[PDB]
Amino acid sequence: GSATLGRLVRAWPRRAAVVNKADILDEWADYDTLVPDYPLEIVPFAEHPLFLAAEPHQRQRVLTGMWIGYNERVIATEQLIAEPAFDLVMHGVFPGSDDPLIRKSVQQAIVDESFHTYMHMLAIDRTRELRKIPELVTYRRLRRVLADMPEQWERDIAVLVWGAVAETCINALLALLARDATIQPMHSLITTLHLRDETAHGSIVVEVVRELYARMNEQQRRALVRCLPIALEAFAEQDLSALLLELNAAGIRGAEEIVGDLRLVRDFSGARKMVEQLGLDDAVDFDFPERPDW
Amino acid sequence: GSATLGRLVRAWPRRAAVVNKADILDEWADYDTLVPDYPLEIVPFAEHPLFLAAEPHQRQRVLTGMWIGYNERVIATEQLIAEPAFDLVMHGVFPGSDDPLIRKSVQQAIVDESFHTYMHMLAIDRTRELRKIPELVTYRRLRRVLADMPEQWERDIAVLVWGAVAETCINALLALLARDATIQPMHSLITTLHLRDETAHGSIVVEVVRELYARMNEQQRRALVRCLPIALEAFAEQDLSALLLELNAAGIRGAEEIVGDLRSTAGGTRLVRDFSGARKMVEQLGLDDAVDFDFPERPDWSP
Image 1 (cartoon, chains in turn blue, cyan):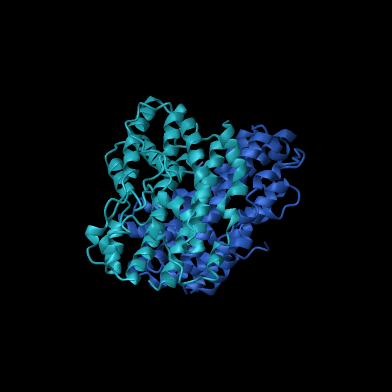
Image 2 (cartoon, rainbow over the protein chains, first blue to last red):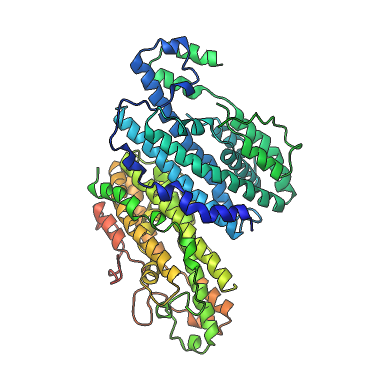
């Protein structure tokens, strides 16, 4: 059995956010309204003259809004992309998925994603309380690939690939929020805890997908190589529709102009590994972006 | 919001099996092969002449297969029935289900179910390795009901009710294996942890279903009322097809004759699910008299 999987399975009790910070709720103890919810320098339009010309409380509303919006996207991703890929691995629908080490490592990740959703949901609800307060462009794609596949087995591949990519391509905001010493300490803790788990999830996915693919027959093998670039591009795309809603919700005049001038890349390093591990360096038409410093 | 739910949600970090025994894998460290996987005391047909006429290793094969089959059904019930009901609540498909407290309680329970599936899966795999080793009837009944409902809103109700019955009506094997000192210590530990979690889940389901039912439109209310007896009877039904297969695997002659009513141990201990919690749920809904179901007597072993 995979020695990486083995190591990650034995290490899970010491590493996992769920085991070690289940009492995340408590972190809103000695609360300070005086710290912002989101870092200014990570906001795409932070420097726009129509933004900077908004009133202090308007800007602060936008930052709060985007902290919230980020948690909503995280939850959507786990529930709609990531978990379902893990679930399919656990339903035993792919050859080679009965292996006990795959079952252990993947089900631990399922526990992790459930707790991630809890952490982020708590963060939304606590923020909305203390601050007195749109479909993902990755899920919409997915729903449209599936709608044109008449056989279950092919939908299985698409779900699997979409989840694998989601789990190996780290959101810049996750790593940026984790290390930010200027925002609410519980915002950077939640994101740090999530990043710690997500690191192991990337290694896990690379192993599992390597094993399933080796054991996929041909309709499943060629299905997968087709799907990957469609999935990777979907996580590469940029829709600023969410930015527009946050701007309008804060009543920022010229919201459309700001977004218009706009017209944070994921760390595709894990998906690159996964491609090399599957031996597909030359077979997938995608231009892997330069690795970030985070 | 509900005081009871407030306290369950604050208790979850102290109480949850996932936080108490994440290192459950390590529990197989000084495994003793001589110690049985399942308690003979608890086997409905333990004293059948044909079960006694078998050889001792054949009876041990049956005991191990019964432990495995138990874990397999737990996993199926969680994956196919309990989680999908919790998942619907978290998707906001019911009026009033966007309550932060409801959301907190149900997402905590979802973390729990995911860990329960982990432990039971671990038990199967470790057992199958160390011993060198069909459709749930309740899910079959569910599928039939759903296949004949035209509208999503009504299938949502049905999924919700079936999930609530599963989570309020404690499996007898869960409670009896939990307290059993004669079997592998990891087996009684896993079921003790799951039992601790499940007791809280029953209380949570009662609060949540009451808050949801209160907010449902009239046809949703009517749908839930129709569904309850269907679910209660599905779960009051034990299937013997699995047992039958174990006996045959062990090579025991006259399997069909051996497996009788599975509703009692030979000593008289009740093996039907503890319907206590679903009775409380029906009361909280004000439905004691609108639901046509004869609840069995509460068993001594009830949580």
